[PDB]
Image 1: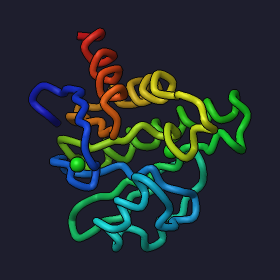
Image 2 (image 1 turned 45 degrees about the horizontal axis):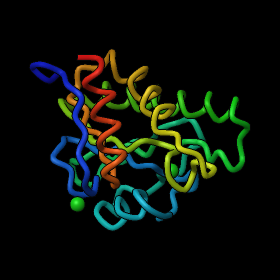
Image 3 (image 1 turned 60 degrees about the vertical axis):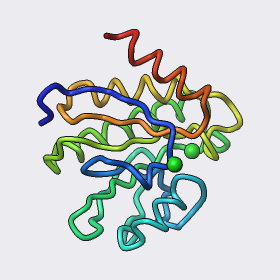
Image 4 (image 1 turned 135 degrees about the vertical axis):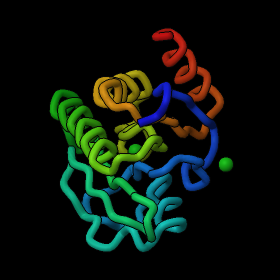
Length: 163
Ligand SMILES: [Cl-]
Ligand SMILES: [Cl-]
């Protein structure tokens, strides 16, 4: 576990993380895909061997000794708001189980279902709150990765409001 488990946020490419494992915003088929998933495929392509897994689940594949946790959020273009919300909460619960099983002291996480899978809605609060629900009981240092300055600002505010 980390000495004083914490949440942080960084505005940079998750493929350049400084943590002991990474969470991929995966597609269910294990394809190279787009956005975070494509960056993860270019950095850790060996981790896409038999990485296909259903919506709401997480599947870990090693790249060397570095764990890639493929977490499949719902595409809100396809799911109802209600069913999508359930599957998004479930994907993060499965990430917490994998982080625990691996024994890592830190994990790099993106906000699931906030990009290509957002159905064109702002889902920062919805996705972050489900990340907290799952990860609050874990002792790994969590570092959230984002792209946009206004996302960094709001994520940082949400973290600090609990401290
Ligand atoms: Cl970067
Ligand atoms: Cl997404």
